[PDB]
Length: 125
Image (cartoon, rainbow, N blue to C red; front, side, top):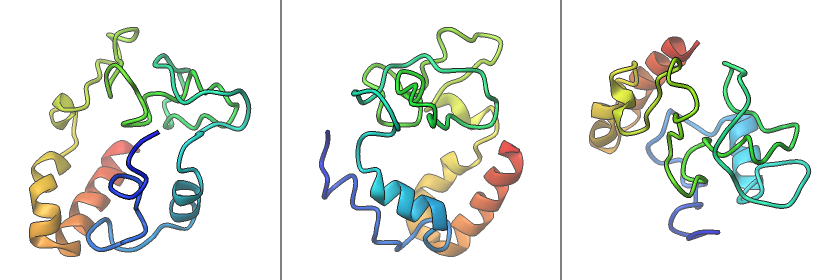
């Protein structure tokens, strides 16, 4: 668990993308914890090769650990996947232009998010 109010309080849409996604707002706000459908846990690390974004729908909650902060060791956990070459703070090289956008998100407001959001969405593929 974590600061339900400080960290999980995602409802204040102020500054972020543009508005509240349909699936994300509900799924994110609804799933303020267990990100799986089956099994009892929070996260593990290793995941399955989907190349579409850790879904963790199968309830391989052990698979849905690299979702972000859920991890306990590292937000990247790219250990077993050197070919894929991953990293969370370092990810700005792989593409994530949003890294510089982090400060710009609140500084520039939505206008900056819309640009970096559309940019990351297209780059992510």
